[PDB]
Image (cartoon, coloured by chain):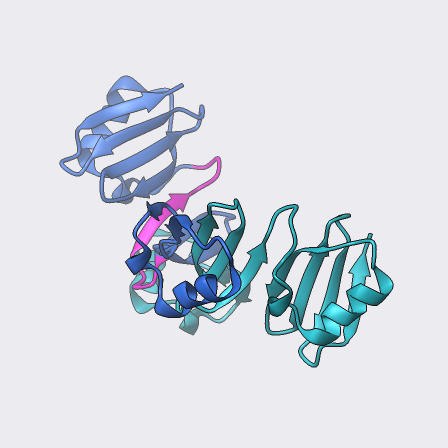
Chain colours: A cyan, B blue
Amino acid sequence: GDVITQDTKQLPLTARNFINQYFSKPHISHIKIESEILQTKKYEVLLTDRTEIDFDKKGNWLEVDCKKSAVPEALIPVPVKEYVKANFPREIITKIERGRTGVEIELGNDYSLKFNKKGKFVSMDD
Amino acid sequence: GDVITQDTKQLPLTARNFINQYFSKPHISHIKIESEILQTKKYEVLLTDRTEIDFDKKGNWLEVDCKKSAVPEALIPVPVKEYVKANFPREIITKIERGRTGVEIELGNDYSLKFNKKGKFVSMDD
């Protein structure tokens, strides 16, 4: 529900005929086209150790939330793993999310860090 | 995002292998399947007389909101039209919505009335 247009040709013939038939002043002052809300996440799995994992329709993981415990080290990319072990040695990674931009990790002290696809740092927030 | 299951066979093979590979205690305590959010409304049209109309992907109207003015009488089913002219003669219909259950109308005094497909009264709220 983001695109807006003033072009009446965009609107289906049945809709245009409906407006012209039932409304006296039938001047269309813009049309909002509801873009289909396409969700990437289809599955959400809760484990017995209370850790939650989100997967897309093909079973590829998207988010791994280990709540207040540590994310298995094998899941965290080496440059990300090494950045945290250097700049935050007092802390552990509790949540990792992967997307098209890269990877976003969350620490035990609620610091969030964003890394790109190549694995180098981008930004963070306190 | 409504269905929940304890059946691991529901979850894709790639997701199941991911859990078994990276997690030591990999007991899946239920899976939430995100049911696809299928929206019936695709178009929303604003007219110059400030009245708003919502249509499905095929151009069939779903809602006609004439804000504080009257809905064109030709749009309101005759049994609905006659019910209002009888029980609410001091009032006018400002909004009409059609669905699978029937029709839901809104009056100028914010009373909402619900009618079935056959056109007879069902309920209302002050």
Q: Position of residue A53 (x, y in %)?
A: 51, 56
Q: Is residue A109 left or right of residue B11?
A: right
Q: Residue at x 35, y 60 (%)?
A: B11
Which image quarter: residue B125?
A: top left
**A82 lies above or below B109:** below
Report the front residue among B44 and B107.
Answer: B44
Report the front residue among A45 and B72.
Answer: A45
Q: Residue at x 60, y 51 (%)?
A: A66
Which image quarter: residue B102?
A: top left
Q: Position of residue B115 (x, y in %)?
A: 23, 31
Q: Which residues are magenta?
A: B56-69
**B83 lies above or below A12:** above
Can residue B61 be found in the magenta stretch?
A: yes
Q: Position of residue A26 (x, y in %)?
A: 42, 57
Q: Is residue B87 visible?
A: yes
Number of marks: 0
Report the front residue among A21 and A50.
Answer: A50
Can residue B117 be found in the magenta stretch?
A: no
Report the front residue among A12 and B22.
Answer: B22
Which image quarter: residue B43?
A: bottom left
Determine the residue located farthest toward the front in the rendered image: B24
Q: Residue at x 22, y 25 (%)?
A: B122
Q: Is residue A52 left or right of residue B125?
A: right
Q: Position of residue B7 (x, y in %)?
A: 30, 52
Q: Is residue A39 visible?
A: no
Q: Is residue A34 left or right of residue B40?
A: right
